[PDB]
């Protein structure tokens, strides 16, 4: 199941960043994303949460395909710094990976943003491959 890629993405991103939590939001043009995977300090109960595409950093990344570091991200963020990482495949964004810190954590560095951008690119390739393997079966 390609969706299983997203579980691994959330888990590996937690490990690589050491952030309090992670989440992956995926389209169910889309008007909404759905949180299919959470890890760390993001409560399990947040899974299946619907996020609007418009008017927030996560939905914006889904549209503009621009990796971004933030000093503050509120719900579904934890109030502190975040990395917003679109999972950019060739003609489609598979979803958005978000690494989240609680308030008063140090901001993410440019190097961390660069590292996780490459991770997020590699992740979308993995997902695009899984999607294609499924489609021809």
Image: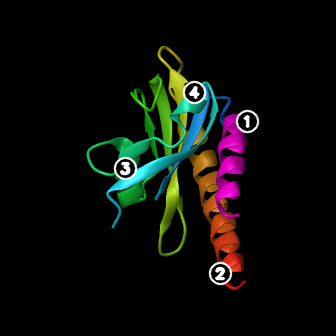
Query: Residue at label 1?
Result: 15
Label 3, label 2: how far apart the Cα atoms are: 27 Å
Locate the N terminus by quadrant.
Answer: bottom right
SS of the residue under disc 1:
helix
Q: How many marks?
A: 4
Give the percent coordinates (x, y) of residue 77. 46, 30
Other-residue count near label 1 (Cα within 10 Å), few / some / many at <14 / 14–19 / ≥20 = few
User: Gap between marks 3 and 1, in whole Å?
Assistant: 24 Å
User: Which numbered mark, 3 or 4, is in the foreground of this view?
Assistant: 4
Residue drawn at 46 percent across, 59 percent down: 28
Q: Which mark is residue 135?
A: 2
Look at the image and give the residue range highlighted in magenta: 1-16
Label 2 crowding class (10 Å Cα cut-off): few <14, some 14-19, many 20+? few
Q: Mark 3 points at which residue?
A: 59
Mark 1 / mark 2, whichever is N-terminal: 1
Q: Nearer the viewer, mark 3 or mark 2?
A: 2
Q: Real-space Cα distance between discs 3 and 4? A: 20 Å
Q: Position of residue 119 (x, y in %)?
A: 65, 52
User: What is the secondary structure assignment of the residue under circle 3?
Assistant: helix
Q: Contact (CB < 8 A) between labels 3 and 2? A: no
């Amino acid at each position: 199941d390609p969706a299983t890629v997203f579980r691994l993405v959330a888990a590996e991103a937690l490990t690589l960043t050491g952030a309090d939590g992670t989440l992956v939001a995926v389209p169910a043009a889309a008007e909404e994303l759905v949180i299919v995977e959470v890890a760390g300090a993001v409560p399990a109960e947040v899974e299946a949460s619907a996020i609007p595409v418009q008017d927030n950093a996560i939905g914006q990344a889904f549209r503009d395909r621009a990796p971004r570091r933030l000093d503050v991200l509120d719900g579904p963020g934890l109030g502190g710094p975040a990395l917003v990482l679109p999972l950019r495949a060739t003609d489609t964004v598979a979803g958005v990976l978000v690494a989240v810190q609680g308030s008063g954590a140090r901001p993410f560095t440019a190097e961390q943003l660069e590292m996780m951008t490459g991770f997020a690119d590699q992740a979308a390739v993995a997902w695009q491959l899984a999607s294609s393997q499924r489609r021809m079966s």
